[PDB]
Image 1 (cartoon, rainbow over the protein chains, first blue to last red):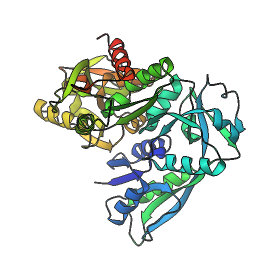
Image 2: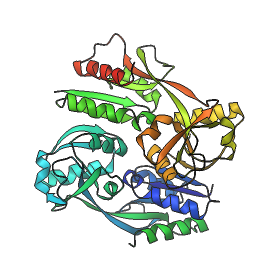
Image 3: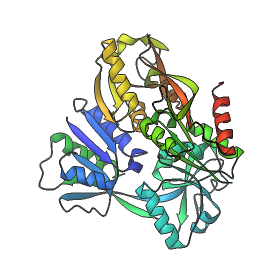
Length: 202
Length: 203
């Protein structure tokens, strides 16, 4: 194998795709392996040299891993263009109380965070639908007048979808690139790192 | 105004379940829905333990306590972007796979397993340059490259930039099925769901 990549669920919906596409077009000779998994798994596998690169969020728990700040992803209210709030670019955080949501199941870290900071903010929106797949959530949102909580970037990837900013912010996480320290990377791994970083410089 | 737990195999998530769940929700907004995609072995098991109300997978069903209602016929196609050299065709010879550089689902997936099986059976050994454990990742990769993939043609009708090329002869054809535990009485939500799923397939 030439390059094993693992990322937490959300990056699969807007980040890793465009990146691996570019990487492949540049170094077609390198075969790629991509797996979306929980940060615990990514960290574990990187320590066991079962993965070359990882993408997750701070803080990193394993001391043997190095973390390179990638980007700051903040959750937003993702809706269809026909959702009554779509007319806005930003709405009060208090708007969530009346939102009927479609959320990822507890399995996902994002959901976990949503629950934590919602209760923290005194917000208890009604979860009418739950799914264990981001795409399913997006699919349901496109066809309904419901909403979801996901990083804003995912919305820029779909026309019928729009990300509404929350004021004040519910959750903001720092995306990071993970690799095992004191471990020499292949030329592929290094070019990967570089490219990932060049993409977040815009 | 209660609940309804649904589970489907990976491929249905990318074209079937979404539109159906949205319709069901608009029709019966009081019912809270639970959707989970997983291996058929898990769906079957969970249905047996009354942990799921409805399942969607393929024939043959292994568990004898489960009932199986034929839903539709899903056949694998070569899915590519519109800028893919073969996109101009609607159907191509199965032999064209030898020259295709693919992006496929990993072994974890049943579809992948099937592909590897019938490919070998057909004497086809295409080169897999990229593997992922998510259909969306595969599709995302195909849209931005000139690579192809093997997935049920329907998936393509959900994306503009994508197109499904029919294979002649066909590589794989599976029978989609609705799963529920027999001798088990369904809720009104479960029943209405079953109905809607069938109305959508002209079944």
